Image: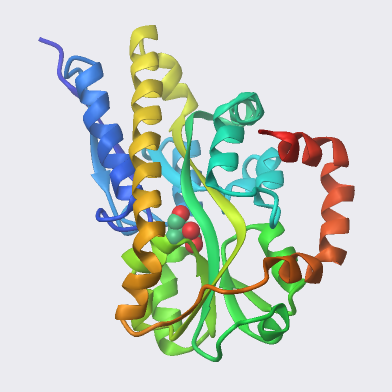
Length: 304
Ligand SMILES: CC(C)(CO)[C@@H](O)C(=O)[O-]
């Protein structure tokens, strides 16, 4: 009898997180939907690499699958940059609808020519600013903060627009950098801040919600293409189910997160005027309009 094929998938976050739910659900569904013919071993906390290294590894084929935020993706697939524009998405429902519908479907196609099968869009969440130095109540309070960023050119340009001094770093370095005070802060969804225990190394958090962070199930293209057609469908369907449970965990994290982090001693600013943060980014946003075009930005904004 043919040997079960085993593949590996990893993330940079904890098993007990929104992304751990994503990959564990995916793995369970692949095994079920392929009648046990495929099995997926799951790795966490940047085992097998943090996100950029892992996306590269999947492209090379050194392991088969990864689940990553959109953060490091533009280096590989430039077309996703528009998703990383600050304040583009009104809320999670808007973002999820865009990604699941034809706009997001078109973006999945852009991975094919770069050596991936992008199985499905999933979610990291809306990102929020934390730091060790001071409470952030207005955009001016961000000026001069030394902040870690992802390896993403849109985020870096945007945050420089707030006067932040940016340091791109792989996620596997971040807890220690915060602890050592190399940087004052970072930015991430509540799902990450909670699961990574950043309350232990960050006194301040503001719910700026300044960008939406999608995530992706990625597979090596050559490997995906060699699967029998029915198993290709099983992998896609498993990824979509992983996205569903992932998003549900994000919802739970976002609902409980302010109370959870306050109880852990963080000062959490959840009353800001977001419109002032948008206004502060006007010059950078004018650049993004020139870069992406009004047509593409309005196409996303129009979405229901
Ligand atoms: C935590 C993370 C790896 C999750 O995708 C990402 O948001 C990041 O690098 O900050």
